[PDB]
Length: 52
Length: 52
Image 1 (cartoon, rainbow over the protein chains, first blue to last red):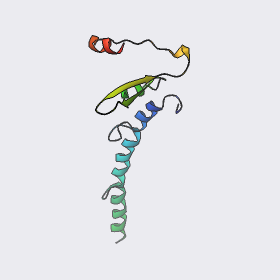
Image 2 (cartoon, helix red, strand yellow; image 1 turned 120 degrees about the vertical axis):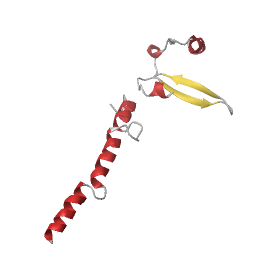
Image 3 (tube, rainbow over the protein chains, first blue to last red; image 1 turned 180 degrees about the vertical axis):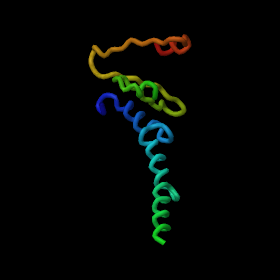
Image 4 (cartoon, helix red, strand yellow; image 1 turned 90 degrees about the horizontal axis):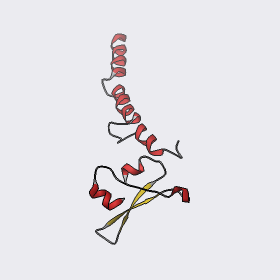
């Protein structure tokens, strides 16, 4: 595929690289979980508060 | 050029900078007399009379 239809793979994986592309979507998706007061942040804060 | 190259079908387009303030489209297929091309346009006669 890389030898033959490279451009198609480029478009599918990253597209424009701003909102289209699987990796581009993953960027925002994972950043959502990693953001401050994210899901993990809330879980950790709740455990900390409970320990009090 | 982009809409040609994206297809990744074996025919590719490159833009050559003629002198200055001028450019020329350059198209090439893979080697072989069997790769000789016939080309035309649909919809736009202005462009067909230029590129056919």
